[PDB]
Length: 121
Image 1 (cartoon, rainbow, N blue to C red):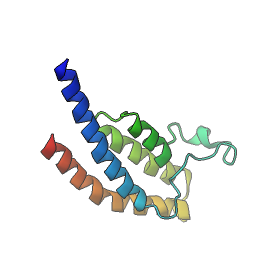
Image 2: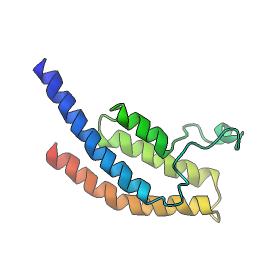
Image 3: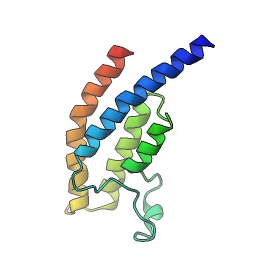
């Protein structure tokens, strides 16, 4: 149907905008602490602590399969990256502190992304 195509075009354009958002958030992580999944070879107890691991590569795979239907879904995954780290790692660690800085800096990007998603529809 033509309606299905129109919906698919909207999803494609959301995917374009989320790709730009993802790039901007990941620039706020110059140390690349959040770039890849926590290695279960190197942290074998991780899943005992963290039930839903997340990282920027995993988000990028979902994104390129057009797997985010709305901004809320995308934000959920970004919040997991932050929140998982702030639980697993103590306050005095470079990991925790990196997550705080990512959250603070990402807030700015996400605020304007929400306006754009609503504005363009």
